[PDB]
Image (cartoon, rainbow, N blue to C red):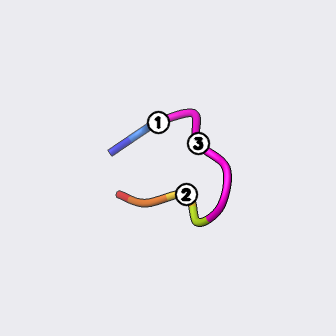
């Protein structure tokens, strides 16, 4: 995906 997380950053 294109996200905004911490911590991993996933698809």
Q: Which mark is residue 5?
A: 3
Q: Are marks 3 and 1 in contact (CB under 8 Å)?
A: yes
Q: Which mark is residue 3?
A: 1
Q: Which residue is mark 2?
A: 9
> Which stretch appears magenta?
3-7
Instruction: Compute the Cα span from label 2 to label 1.
Output: 7 Å
Q: Are marks 2 and 3 in contact (CB under 8 Å)?
A: yes
**Is residue 4 left or right of 11 when viewed as pictured?**
right
Number of marks in the rendered image:
3
Binning the other alpha carbons within 10 Å of mark 3 as few (below 14), some (14 to 19) or many (20 upward) gives few
Query: Residue at coordinates 35% horizontally, 57% vertically from top-left?
Result: 11
Q: Are marks 2 and 1 in contact (CB under 8 Å)?
A: yes
**Element carrying mark 3:** loop
Magenta-colored segment: predominant secondary structure: loop
Where, by quadrant of the figure, is residue 1 drawn?
Answer: top left
Instruction: Compute the Cα span from label 3 to label 1.
Output: 6 Å
């Amino acid at each position: 995906x294109l996200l905004v997380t911490a911590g991993l950053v996933l698809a």
